Length: 114
Length: 114
Image (cartoon, rainbow over all chains, first blue to last red; front, side):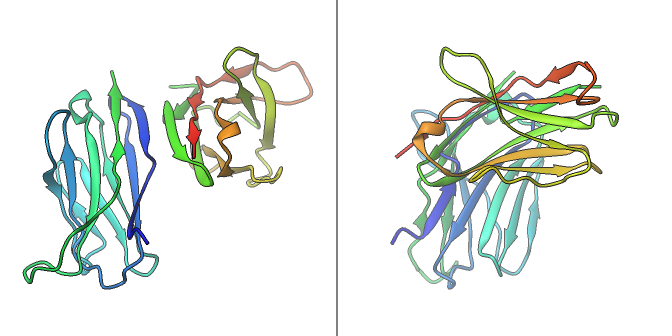
């Protein structure tokens, strides 16, 4: 029973092209969903979050579309730059603040060809 | 204007996963959208197709969703069997019947593994 399904596994794209990384979870108690960016030879790094209260989080071309009812959210990378070539992790937690362990996704690797 | 643009460029999905290969056409006059299945060393074989009048099509675990409004199109390979690992091409022509040119996209590589 792995609770943070990520799709797809690998994905290549074009420079400027918009990449879409999906995530689905089962534990309905999940209310805090952080995405981590991981460059080669490094560990995860907070990239962008989204609280179950909202539906979308805006950042500089990083947007987290989230759907509570259907329990599916997604990272949308507008204008995919070759810098964004990293591994993206979708993690879900039942709460931020009181230590409720973070359930990670297996990750979706990206590659932005120029 | 980009004739026919296919995104992503490559994928990788788990066996049994539903794969979505998108296609985008710039010319509104395009009324015939065929999809090909190209294997590692062979030639592209017409896998499935749809007309501008129809906006959905079932071959069997194969669906072409066609949104003529946005000029968006997409092939969904349901239950992505690892055998579906191939390069898929989106093509679009102004008409079927008469000898109108098929403007070929550039294909999305699919790698499905268990």
